[PDB]
Image (cartoon, rainbow, N blue to C red; front, top):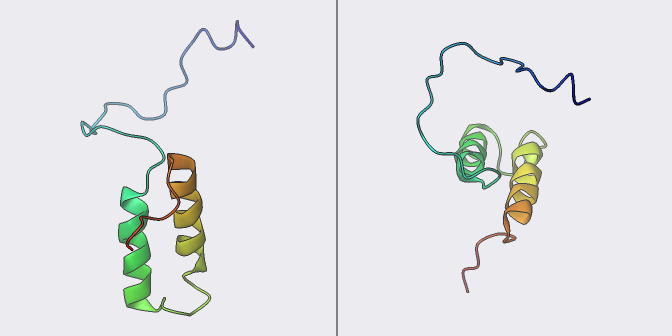
Length: 69
């Protein structure tokens, strides 16, 4: 496990992403969710994936859904 991790794995040759990655968050999840809703989401059982995934995402971040009040 140590002598097999000493080397790299190589996922993609020549990088192309310069933007930072805060990890977890839900920045992209929000866009994808809204998109699905625009298509056929709303109440259909084809958008529950984005909704549930969004909830868990923010949960791991540090806050469960942005408070409005």
